[PDB]
Amino acid sequence: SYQPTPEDRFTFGLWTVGWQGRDPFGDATRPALDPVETVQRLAELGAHGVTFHDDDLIPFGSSDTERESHIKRFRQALDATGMTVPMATTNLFTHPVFKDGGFTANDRDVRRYALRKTIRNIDLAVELGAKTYVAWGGREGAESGAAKDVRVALDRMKEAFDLLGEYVTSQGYDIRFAIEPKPNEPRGDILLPTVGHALAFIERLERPELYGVNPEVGHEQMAGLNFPHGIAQALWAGKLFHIDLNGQSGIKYDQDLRFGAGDLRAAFWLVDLLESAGYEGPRHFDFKPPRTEDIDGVWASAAGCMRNYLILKERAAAFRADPEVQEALRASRLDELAQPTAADGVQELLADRTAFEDFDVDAAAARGMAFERLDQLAMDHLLGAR
Amino acid sequence: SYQPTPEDRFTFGLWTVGWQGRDPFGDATRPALDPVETVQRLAELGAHGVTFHDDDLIPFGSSDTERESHIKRFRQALDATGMTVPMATTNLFTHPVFKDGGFTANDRDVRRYALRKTIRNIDLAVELGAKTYVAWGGREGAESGAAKDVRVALDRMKEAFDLLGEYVTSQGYDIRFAIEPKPNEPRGDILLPTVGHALAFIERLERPELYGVNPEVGHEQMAGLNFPHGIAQALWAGKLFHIDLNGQSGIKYDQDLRFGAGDLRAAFWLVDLLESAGYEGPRHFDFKPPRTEDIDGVWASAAGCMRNYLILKERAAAFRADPEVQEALRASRLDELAQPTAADGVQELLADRTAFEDFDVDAAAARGMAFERLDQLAMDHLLGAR
Amino acid sequence: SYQPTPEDRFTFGLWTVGWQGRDPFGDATRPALDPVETVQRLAELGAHGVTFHDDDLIPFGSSDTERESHIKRFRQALDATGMTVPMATTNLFTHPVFKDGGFTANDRDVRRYALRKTIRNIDLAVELGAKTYVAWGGREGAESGAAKDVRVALDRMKEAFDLLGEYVTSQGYDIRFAIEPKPNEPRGDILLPTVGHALAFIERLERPELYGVNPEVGHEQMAGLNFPHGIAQALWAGKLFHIDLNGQSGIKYDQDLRFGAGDLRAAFWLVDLLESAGYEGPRHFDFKPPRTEDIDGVWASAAGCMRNYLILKERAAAFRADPEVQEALRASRLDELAQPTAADGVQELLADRTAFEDFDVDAAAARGMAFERLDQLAMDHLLGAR
Amino acid sequence: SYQPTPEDRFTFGLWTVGWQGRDPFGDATRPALDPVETVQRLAELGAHGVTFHDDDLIPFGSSDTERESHIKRFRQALDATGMTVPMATTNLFTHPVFKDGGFTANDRDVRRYALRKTIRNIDLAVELGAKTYVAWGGREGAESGAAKDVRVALDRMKEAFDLLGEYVTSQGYDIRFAIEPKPNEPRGDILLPTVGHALAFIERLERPELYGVNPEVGHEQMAGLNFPHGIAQALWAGKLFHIDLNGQSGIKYDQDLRFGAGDLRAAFWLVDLLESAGYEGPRHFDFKPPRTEDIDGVWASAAGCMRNYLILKERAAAFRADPEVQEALRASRLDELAQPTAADGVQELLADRTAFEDFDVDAAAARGMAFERLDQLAMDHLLGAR
Ligand SMILES: OC[C@H]1O[C@H](O)[C@H](O)[C@@H](O)[C@@H]1O
Ligand SMILES: OC[C@H]1O[C@H](O)[C@H](O)[C@@H](O)[C@@H]1O
Ligand SMILES: OC[C@H]1O[C@H](O)[C@H](O)[C@@H](O)[C@@H]1O
Ligand SMILES: OC[C@H]1O[C@H](O)[C@H](O)[C@@H](O)[C@@H]1O
Ligand SMILES: [Mn+2]
Ligand SMILES: [Mn+2]
Ligand SMILES: [Mn+2]
Ligand SMILES: [Mn+2]
Ligand SMILES: [Mn+2]
Ligand SMILES: [Mn+2]
Ligand SMILES: [Mn+2]
Ligand SMILES: [Mn+2]
Ligand code: NA
Ligand code: NA
Ligand code: NA
Ligand code: NA
Ligand code: NA
Ligand code: NA
Ligand code: NA
Ligand code: NA
């Protein structure tokens, strides 16, 4: 039961299971993992593919010979296992040069370097099959108010993304960009801190159709937001190009717990939404096996991400298929929410005395929404106690 | 010193100083205020104008004769004092009929009522001179996951705002809408929870030019976000149609403290930004005098909102005018942030070896940003210890 | 399955199911409930008892004749159903007189009134059978820094609790006090904001044995704290005299969702802890049926509180009984945590070279904790997918 | 103006200005600092002393010869500058051996090692003059619910602290312990997460008089708590043995901004409280110069910590000395808060009809607290606009 296979589209970053366990107050607890080992182990667990930052695959500062070698061993592992690479990204955050940003660094020469580093890796991503290229502007932001003029920084961010869009267009590449929001950490405040801010920004790019979001469960939860709601807004906009699945225990540092951990009911509602919307993209885990774990715990935690998705998928499907739930949804007027409010138009609404002058507000007010009964059916289904 | 006059554009909602002090665990501590008294007292304190919900000005359920009477006394007070009404809004949250929303109520008849209630008050707002009409969807959202299908709710929200835009267009009215985000309270999660989400949503309306945001200091801070940053993004988008100024002590219930209270340095950076951007709109306070206060404390707290703005304006101006600060800004490369990254374009960037192959990442990395010295000049200016 | 009976010790405040739905932005959505109706309906659902504030049972300002009448009808309902009253409390928060506090009001005459109001209700509580008397100092605190000298306020709080302890001692009453922490709301910050602060304060009372805590799930979660951990510390101290069970969706206003809602895995770990510790007190729900609900939804939500406890109890028991979990606990050294570190004492520890000079830190470091496998067994048990 | 000198008691950890800038997503941005250089630079800035973890002063794993060398160079620098060492602590968090804790590690051999490591450094601390020995249990806690039995962990924590108290007592050392709370990070939840929880725990130690708290501004703010209030409770308990001063911008990762940054008004109220209470201990900064900074920015940020304390001290003194503020305090009944509520005792209170039967609740309720006027005087003083 609940055994993943490649059909389930589960993917993992090299940096997830490969995290050595260094944290702000601690040294590594595990050795570096060879990307080849990660591809093989994830394939054996039932994954569909892996993702990478440039610098996870090729050590920063590698010579061209070393680069080619690292790429060849990785491609051979992919080819041997049938593992795919649906997404890639750039590391614009680890090296000290990026201490004030990549695309929005105050130093212009750093901004140009950030773009060149990104473009090099776009070319590699395309060759390996990535259809989405993620940008996580983790260093874009500030600890203090005058350090960053945010309007001007947004000009530089737009310029950078427009330059990347011109590049991909000129090369004829079939790849799209996905902006991954995060509200803070490692900057005191990060630019484009939520799904909303990223969606809004995209609409001022030159070629908005080339850009979407890569929301992460834990990141929206670091702002105390409802992740399923934000995903719904991204889906409504047509912009859910990729997703990062994990867990987070509230408003704190970015934990990157395995999926299912943290806010379990939000994980349930997320899976319910992805499945009923027909999301077709990768089910990507951006998680960290806690540094308490040895390598065997790394693979257990990775397996748990997939298992939890599959359990939740089963429970959500059972919830929506239950005739008692379909009745409760009617009792709560979820069907009526889908009716247009005023397809008859403004003049007909204005002339309709049943909408105002003769509307019995007290009788309407007295009608309960029946949401608690509906939610307890949902609880029962999640818990297998339906 | 720091004496407000109407030239300063300070405005207040009737419901601010008029708050009787009822909270989730407490009865009223002050009597209801007559709108006429509020207009006169605010005028004497140096305010420029007032704002209202329909139901603050005219008691809900008033007959047409009573309505006209309430409106006439208010207009006479405005006319006598020279107080203006730059903004108005609808109460789509107090009456029990709105328990599941106005525009996104699951019951269709409630959605239609919400629109009619809004349209009636738009007509009044225009007559009184409001150029901005605020929508705060405080009841739009959910406590539980299946209660609200958010994609469908967003369809209903869009339909409602598009209907209002068709109405104002057909009447030829010179008024614009401003959506006021809030992340939660009184719903467990509110739709369009931040400035970003509201900006994003606007871009999918039929007539996006008619809609902007009315961000509130405390509301973005209820998500732990940086209010000056969010205002910067709204300004960058051309969408800061109005603002609500107040204070908030962290991630908790909506406090609506007087402006300056709560996060004082964020208040400083906000004023710095509004003044350097040339924001021309009302400086509107959406605050609650704490229920500890009697009527004399109400007016003290209102006066304090204005005084704090004026003090912060002076300090921010002194900061930006100080030659030592202008040097520190250069030292921190704020000037260089404004240079285009690659106006030379993609081919020139790709051919520029100084951007990649020959870029000395370590020398760049070693250069300090000097942000702490800059921020301590800012601190010194705020504290008057420059 | 999961049918509550009085043996399960479930109790509810009159103010829970009796909440009329007034919130900071909304009028009542339900009529007032007669306490007699609440006793009868809860008894039919399988509850064991009810709790009350003075002013829930007897309207504030009732004459002595009216008081006696309200008490008699309630006692007759209790007597008819076999419902108990294990806890009572005072309302020191609704009336405007308490706007700056009860026991720590700056006005001395208010502090004295608060004590008299409390003592009157202690006498009633004892007659009705309450063994715990809760104090929730919801108005004790401040919105601003100089309004409340906290050291002096703590002196007044101690004086009040010591006076109450002298009263109960002199009357020979068998009742204990339980302080209910909350971090904020309705005050900007509330004194004794967490379980820890309340436990600490108790140790400086004259008769500390008479005082414990009444922690509430949602209140500790309003500080982002781990409720099971705080309960563990209260149990460790011998101070878990009562508990309030509910749900909360993060760091925000006090939601008082039904138990099980909000942080579901924290609800699981809480039940696991209460059951393995042998907590014998009431399983009391301090919740609000959302104001979306009519009366039928009130009773559904109340029933859901009890059902969720019972489901979680079953899952937690199954988890701890599973041989695979008992093995995983050993693999993770939970057994070894219970061994004394150094029962051999300080001189033997200092002379033990295996504790320092000859301790192989790297071999110890390399041993994984196996916590992820353990936690995934816990997840599987919660979800019924063991 | 605002020039620190040793008389001001300012101290800094070696790890503060010595932070190399590694964060969870970034490599070091600055070179390691020699402790000798730190002592000399801080002395030149006007500091009084420095603090250390064992492993900041002596590299982990140093041979006895290397240890003695590191200690000698440091003592020579101290001796040359007149810099003191008022506090020391153990690093029980960086090495991978401590991945599940020191004193509460599930592995018993790790717990014993943690104690030996601590005892070795106590002996050094005493020699160097430390009068306070801090314990920060940053690894004590869990990411998952079954990983740590908190009651049993508290038994192990108590055992460890009792063993340390027996050791210091047997050696005759004049040193006290201070527990530094933090709610989370690097563990998902940390044991003893707040000042309150630590104060409570101390009262169950064998020799409670030997233990107090070392609260940190940012740590209490990571739980959204009021730091001045928590300090007031620690002072009220007689347990403020040391303090860590810094800044924090809300509920997020531990930022360790320079003091004054983050919540500026809380910094003001903190200084007001420390000065009026007569706190005599070190004014210790536990801060991180942001990794954006080079070495010159390190010393600017360190200097800014001290400058901000001194500015705030001046403003707080001016506030309390202002006759207008002393009148406002009376208007707000801060004087009356200091009067005993019922020194006349319980029988006299019960017989006093002015406390209940004849108390005019409405007249009392109608009296405003005048807190807003008081707080605006405080604002004016902070801003130098009095
Ligand atoms: O962009 C891919 C990844 O970059 C970094 O690893 C971020 O920490 C992570 O959240 C993001 O998903
Ligand atoms: O929309 C105007 C106002 O409506 C309500 O009063 C909200 O509480 C407030 O935040 C909003 O600004
Ligand atoms: O003290 C009993 C109750 O008083 C109030 O109703 C509080 O809101 C609640 O949290 C508390 O449990
Ligand atoms: O215990 C002294 C220090 O140990 C670590 O450096 C912690 O991060 C810090 O908060 C604490 O004060
Ligand atoms: Mn993350
Ligand atoms: Mn991610
Ligand atoms: Mn507000
Ligand atoms: Mn507002
Ligand atoms: Mn509550
Ligand atoms: Mn409660
Ligand atoms: Mn810290
Ligand atoms: Mn610290
Ligand atoms: Na590689
Ligand atoms: Na573009
Ligand atoms: Na009126
Ligand atoms: Na439109
Ligand atoms: Na009654
Ligand atoms: Na006592
Ligand atoms: Na050294
Ligand atoms: Na002891």
Image (cartoon, coloured by chain):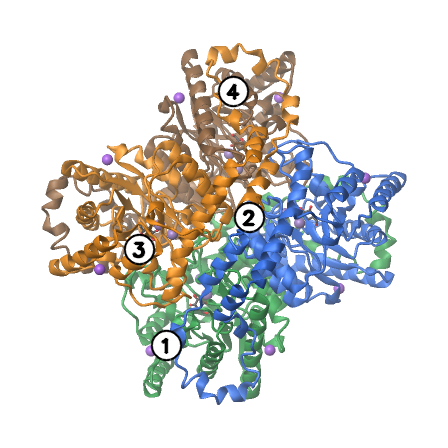
Chain colours: A brown, B orange, C green, D blue
Question: Residue placed at 27% from the left, 46% from the top?
Answer: B86
**Whether the residue under disc 3 has CB within 8 Å of ligand 15:** no
- Quarter of the figure with residue B163: top left
Residue type of the residue flagged with mark 4: Leu
Q: Disc 3 on helix, strand or loop?
A: helix
Measure the C-alpha gap from mark 4 to mark 1.
Answer: 69 Å
Q: Quadrant of residue C294?
A: bottom left
Which element carries disc 1, helix, strand or loop? helix
Which residue position is annotated with label 4?
A115
Instruction: Judge the density around disc 2: few (<14), some (14-19), many (≥20) Cα neighbours within 10 Å.
Output: many
In the rendered image, which residue does mark 1 sit on?
D362
Which of pointers 2 and 3 lies earlier in the amino acid sequence?
A: 3
User: Picture coordinates of residue D182 (x, y %)?
Assistant: 62, 52
Front in this rendered view, residue B326 or A99: B326
Up-down: is A9 above or below A333? above
**Residue tagged by mark 2?**
B383
Same-chain status of marks 4 and 2 = no
Q: Is mark 4 within 8 Å of ligand 14?
A: no
Would you call the spot at circle 1 few (<14 residues within 10 Å), some (14-19), or many (20 or more)? few
Between C38 and C144, which is closer to the camera in this rendering?
C144
| Amino acid type, residue under disc 3 in the picture | Ala
Label 1 or label 3, whichever lies nearer to me, is 3
Q: Which residue is mark 3?
A: B43
